[PDB]
Figure 1 (cartoon, rainbow over the protein chains, first blue to last red):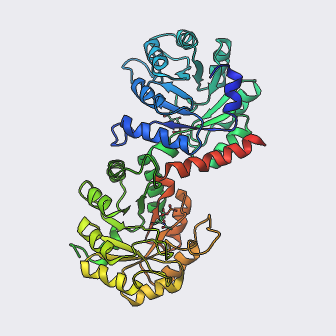
Figure 2 (cartoon, rainbow over the protein chains, first blue to last red):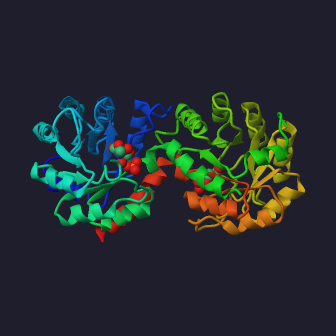
Figure 3 (cartoon, rainbow over the protein chains, first blue to last red):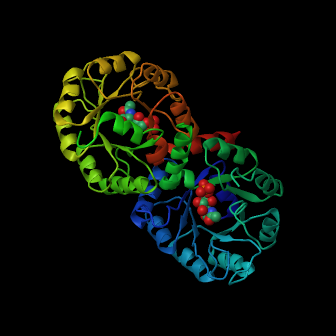
Length: 223
Length: 230
Ligand SMILES: CC(=O)N[C@@H](C=O)[C@@H](O)[C@H](O)[C@H](O)COP(=O)([O-])[O-]
Ligand SMILES: CC(=O)N[C@@H](C=O)[C@@H](O)[C@H](O)[C@H](O)COP(=O)([O-])[O-]
């Protein structure tokens, strides 16, 4: 609960489990999402990233650790996907999210990014900016956004984007490392780069993706 | 021999990753419907074989996927260290449940039924036999009995301090002898599972890194928290 720098002692050095199964998968169901949320809490995870108004609602009634809410939408006239409408923001607040993350890139979008960021702050929830570049974070800071993340770097590669984490951290930002941290050792280099916490999704909660990671290596060797 | 021969299975499995779908016991994810869902998912993602635990999980999974199942029943007994399929009644249930290969503990330890009789109960079903071995002698014994598959499953799980890195030497030793070798145990990343194939394994079984969310979660927090306090 309550102020941002209390959230920053709670999240220091933590791994944040982004529970977003593959779309269309047999695993892409609210029950299995809640089950994973209950499970990672028992294993010591202190925070989650959950996608979908009704997934946030289901998970928030079953766990106690903070939830970073998002909604993903494939728009027909824009590349922005992560929470592009204030009406999504309002649902995420109602659903029980502690932080609401949004795409903070300077691209074509149905509603200005200043209004999304300011609509989150209105909720009472913390705001986290999903950034693609260092200057996305400069914009986010000027708008009163509590959290900046490297979520969108490279999605506008294969290794994480560590220098963005270094720049955000030595800018004084409350920095969330997110994107391609696929082993515990890459997530440790994130914290040492100055990130307060690190978000990990595919390596933890996308079984199809990780399965293909192994078969790719074992089949390639099988000559 | 439901419809297959040994060398037909070994080309089907060559260079493949075998997904061990065994949630943590008592976990919210340890449900049959969740196990079947995970089984359907890895098949859709291209996995060619599974290890499934529990007679009724084997039955449920075999009715929903098409890839072969290596069935086991694991029991923690009060008077024996053997865990992997220690009873003849377990073998018969796994065959009826639809498993193609049945894995058993092949170690020379205290056990309710001799390892020879277990192996012979598998053959009676018609299923292929996979020996879960702890030492090279265990696979050599399995060789003398006609067991089709030998695995490094039990290497490091007989003593006290249970290891962290895979045991590549036993996989090489089983491969050097001409055995049809399955590398299994502690292959937790795609490159270590690749070093297993390069070590001569036909296929490789991976469990915790894929289907134990609690375990992998603790793997990350252990590294981020330790640095996060430094
Ligand atoms: C582009 C986009 O939508 N990125 C993320 C949005 O939340 C999402 O796809 C991903 O799960 C997180 O970044 C977690 O990171 P990773 O561990 O999956 O790489
Ligand atoms: C000791 C024992 O009973 N081991 C296996 C039993 O079937 C099982 O617990 C283990 O997950 C597999 O070896 C898969 O290997 P890994 O990926 O979990 O390391």
